Image (cartoon, coloured by chain):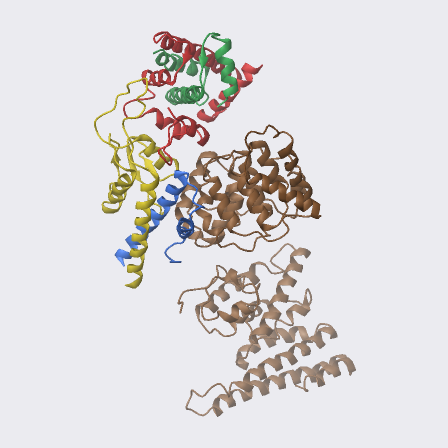
């Protein structure tokens, strides 16, 4: 996990919230599963439309489903 | 011979579980020489014994 | 050297008591005792009991990380190292008070000091703990070099096949994992169902680079009754075949019989039928496709064909019988041969043909020999009679002992020896007809007349 | 007949070694822990000894070889499961990670 | 930029998971997707921290976040995902393990 990089993300965006020891490993466990659910839907949208190269609309249709489940 | 071919498998499974039970326990086994003899005995298979 | 030894005796005796409380002189005293580790070991060396004290402290984590790594870099032993020091040092690593970079320098110490230990009994008995350090990914080239040097036949286990195929599927192709499976195919090929390439790789640290190891040891890569069969490749020299001749398996090809002289001893005493028919089926196809006049007249392939016929003429003389492929090739090449283009390798190929009847040889050999004998040069005319005097050697050598080795037939052998009487008396009277006719061709030259009387010496 | 009676004497030496190493080092776990300043909720199912946990796992695998799966219940403790999973002793089912089994080492 | 090089490790994880070569402006869509997901990660934690009345992130709100996204269910727990997707150094510090004397090195 880039533990030095995740302290730079959490302080520049919201400079009032603190993180304890090994709390960023579950942030990295979230981000390993977020890209893996993004790449699964992008593989699903490419094989259903019979196009091998993943276009920008295959990422954008995956951005309307996977990011919708992230809010709560 | 069927009892031998099942007890060699039982001896192999228990001697390969028990060495990882020694390793996962984090116990200094070098101070006991009889337990050191058990740890040096656990490598030997049914052809050596 | 005694004052350097007595400074070491107060340094090892300070380290075995651990850190001494109520004393804030640890920045000066034990730093000076860390400086006594190098200048004894870089000049003189240490005894075997001085290695055993300092290795147990540096793997337990008493003085920190920066002190214990500087001990492991600069130790040079002068005597043998006991295996009981190797047994206890695993058990201090089983406590769990050790760091990551300290385990690197402990594993690099066992690589470089492997040849100075002659007790490899209890080190091989710790192989189950040596396999179980593969869960750490940062130590993974350092573990697998220790797994290479400590593997026996009983250490190759099928679940250890199964874990390393799972590590091949997760983190891919690495040269420390492919070289560990290359020894496992060198020891037990039946336990692995995944075949490996056989390409030229150095596989490890090799090729005598011990000065390059010591320059990179300062600060580099330290931070993260048997009725079965015997295998043919284990015959290295002469007495390995003398102990095992009654159990010898069959190879994957018959072209390796001519390569090894130890396999030429196996042909001398085995009179089995399908081991001679498969050798007939290979070498008849070798002489037919890779001959001279079937090619596009390459001088380099004719040199390799000359080098292949030098293997045949030493194999026919070591066996003392000619091969059944070789006399079948001369049945088809003597109408197709003119008299040159490796003449000396072709006239020695006719010299070691075994005995047959006289009426079978003369339409296939002696008609096509006499078409070239009276018409070529006199160096060919002398080389025919040098070939036929060696043909009169090996035919009369077989007939001299064929009487001795046959008590089986209860019939008298005077019809068989009388049938062999006119086969060889018409042999000498044909070459004697070749000798008195070629004298008239050259009109009494003495250079042919020396080799006619050498034929009647036989 | 002698060497099959010899390896049973190596078995009863090792099961006495298994009975004495786990008793002196891995005691009975108490469910009345972390009771300072909080009130964490546990069930009334009592935890057992890890030597009694491994006695079930060698009786599940070796008696019926076609079903080694053991359901994780309230009688088990999850660091006792993690000690069997870190060293590679036990393995979970990949379609459902609630059933553990004793992985045999012969293939 | 260090924000660009720190997100480029997850660009190479995105090329590894899809197993296809990806266009450069398509990877700029992913770096804008991870910029707004990390903004929504900080927005979901401040709802979870103001519900308890604190400004320091505790791991039980991280346990609650995967239960609402479907990553942790009644059959797949949080300890399944650590032992299969993270190495041995991260498995030691997160999951409690049992040792001699009933001692736990991540003691709670």
Q: Residue at x 37, y 26 (%)?
A: E81
- What hue represents chain D? yellow
Chain letter matching colour blue = B
User: Relative to the observer, which residue lies in front, C120 or C94?
Assistant: C94
Q: Is residue A44 above or below residue B32?
A: above
In front of the other: C100 or C177: C100
Rendered hue of chain A is green
Question: Residue E27, position in %: x, y?
Answer: 50, 17
**Is residue C59 among what the camera can see?**
yes
Is A31 rendered above or below residue C256? Answer: above
Q: Is residue C337 left or right of residue D25?
A: right
Near-viewer residue (C314 or C174): C174
Which quarter of the rendered picture does the C terminus of chain C lie within? Answer: bottom right
Which residue corresponds to the image point at 45% horizontal and 20% vertical from the top-left?
A21
- Look at the image and give the colour of chain E: red
Residue C146 is situated, as x and y percent measured from the top left of the image, at 52, 46
Q: Residue furthest left?
A: D44
User: How far across and how far down the image is residue C393, in percent?
Assistant: 62, 81
Residue C421 position within the rendered picture, expressed as x and y whole percent measured from the top left: 55, 89
Tint applied to chain C in the drawing: brown
Q: Quadrant of residue E74?
A: top left
Q: Residue at x 52, y 51 (%)?
A: C83
- The relative height of residue C385 versus residue B17 in the rendered view (above or below) is below
- For this view, does C251 lie left or right of residue C212? left
């Amino acid at each position: 996990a880039p533990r030095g990089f995740l302290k730079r993300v959490f302080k520049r965006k919201k400079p009032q919230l603190r993180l304890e020891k090994s709390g960023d490993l579950l942030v990295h466990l979230n981000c390993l599963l977020f890209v893996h659910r993004l790449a699964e839907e992008s593989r699903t949208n490419a094989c259903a439309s019979k196009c091998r190269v993943i276009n920008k609309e295959h990422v954008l249709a995956a951005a309307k489903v996977i990011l919708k489940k992230s809010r709560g | 011979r069927q009892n031998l071919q099942m007890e060699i498998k039982i001896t192999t499974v228990i001697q390969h579980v028990f060495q990882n039970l020694i390793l996962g326990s984090k116990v200094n086994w070098a101070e006991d020489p009889a337990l050191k003899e058990i740890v040096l005995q656990l490598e030997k298979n049914v052809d050596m014994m | 050297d005694q004052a350097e030894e007595d400074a070491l005796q107060m340094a090892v005796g300070y380290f075995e008591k651990g850190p001494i409380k109520a004393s804030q002189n640890k920045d000066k005293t034990l730093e000076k005792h860390l400086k006594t580790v190098e200048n004894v070991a870089w000049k003189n060396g240490l005894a075997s009991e001085e290695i055993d004290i300092l290795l147990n402290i540096a793997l337990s984590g008493k003085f920190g990380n920066a002190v214990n790594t500087r001990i492991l870099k600069c130790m040079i032993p002068a005597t043998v190292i006991s295996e009981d020091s190797v047994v206890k040092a695993v058990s201090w690593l089983c406590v769990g008070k050790c760091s990551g970079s300290t385990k690197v320098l402990f594993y690099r110490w066992l690589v470089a000091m492997f040849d100075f230990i002659d007790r490899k009994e209890q080190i091989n008995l710790l192989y189950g703990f040596f396999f179980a350090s593969l869960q750490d990914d940062a130590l993974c080239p350092y573990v697998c070099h220790l797994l290479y040097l400590l593997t026996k036949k009983e250490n190759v286990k099928p679940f250890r096949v199964r874990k390393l195929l799972d590590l091949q599927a997760k983190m891919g192709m690495q040269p420390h994992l492919q070289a560990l499976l290359s020894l496992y195919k060198f020891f037990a090929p039946a336990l692995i169902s995944v075949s490996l390439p056989v390409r030229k790789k150095i596989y490890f640290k090799n090729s005598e680079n011990l000065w390059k190891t010591a320059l990179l040891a300062v600060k580099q890569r330290n931070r993260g009754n048997r009725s079965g069969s015997f295998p043919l490749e284990q015959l290295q020299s002469f007495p390995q075949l003398l102990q095992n001749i009654h159990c010898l398996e069959l190879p994957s090809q018959m072209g390796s019989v001519l390569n090894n002289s130890l396999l030429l001893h196996y042909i001398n005493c085995v009179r089995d039928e399908p081991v001679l028919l498969r050798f007939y089926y290979w070498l008849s196809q070798t002489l037919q496709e890779e001959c001279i006049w079937y090619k596009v007249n390459n001088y380099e392939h004719g040199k390799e064909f000359t080098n292949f016929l030098d293997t045949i003429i030493r194999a026919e003389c070591f066996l003392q019988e000619g091969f059944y492929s070789c006399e079948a090739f001369l049945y088809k090449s003597l109408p197709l041969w003119d008299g040159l283009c490796c003449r000396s390798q072709f006239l020695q190929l006719v010299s070691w043909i075994p005995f047959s009847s006289f009426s079978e040889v003369k339409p296939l050999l002696f008609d096509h020999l006499a078409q070239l004998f009276f018409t070529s040069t006199i160096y060919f005319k002398c080389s025919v009679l040098q070939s036929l005097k060696e043909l009169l050697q090996n035919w009369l050598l077989w007939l001299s002992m064929d009487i001795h080795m046959k008590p089986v037939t209860n019939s008298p052998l005077e019809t068989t020896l009388g049938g062999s009487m006119n086969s060889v008396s018409k042999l000498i009277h044909y070459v004697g007809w070749l000798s008195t006719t070629a004298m008239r061709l050259e009109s009494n030259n003495t250079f042919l007349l020396h080799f006619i009387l050498d034929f009647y010496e036989k | 007949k002698t060497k099959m009676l010899n390896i049973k004497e190596y078995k009863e030496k090792l099961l006495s070694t298994l009975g004495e190493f786990l008793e002196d080092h891995f005691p009975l776990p108490d469910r009345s822990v972390k009771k300072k300043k909080k009130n964490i909720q546990e069930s009334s199912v009592n935890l057992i000894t890890l030597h009694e946990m491994l006695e079930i796992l060698i009786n599940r695998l070796f008696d019926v070889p076609h079903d080694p799966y053991v359901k994780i219940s309230d009688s088990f403790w999850p660091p006792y499961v993690e000690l069997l999973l870190r060293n590679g002793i036990a393995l979970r089912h990949p379609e459902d990670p609630t059933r553990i089994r004793l992985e045999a080492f012969h293939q | 930029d260090p924000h660009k090089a720190g997100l480029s490790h997850y660009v190479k994880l995105f090329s590894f998971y899809a197993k296809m070569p990806m266009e450069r402006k398509a990877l700029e869509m992913v770096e804008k997707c991870l910029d707004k997901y990390f903004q929504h990660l900080c927005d979901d934690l401040e709802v979870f921290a103001a519900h308890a009345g604190r400004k320091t992130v505790k791991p039980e709100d991280l346990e609650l976040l995967m239960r609402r996204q479907g990553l942790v269910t009644d059959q797949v727990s949080l300890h399944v995902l650590v032992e299969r997707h993270l190495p041995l150094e991260y498995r030691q510090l997160l999951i409690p393990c049992a040792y001699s004397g009933n001692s736990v090195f991540p003691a709670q």
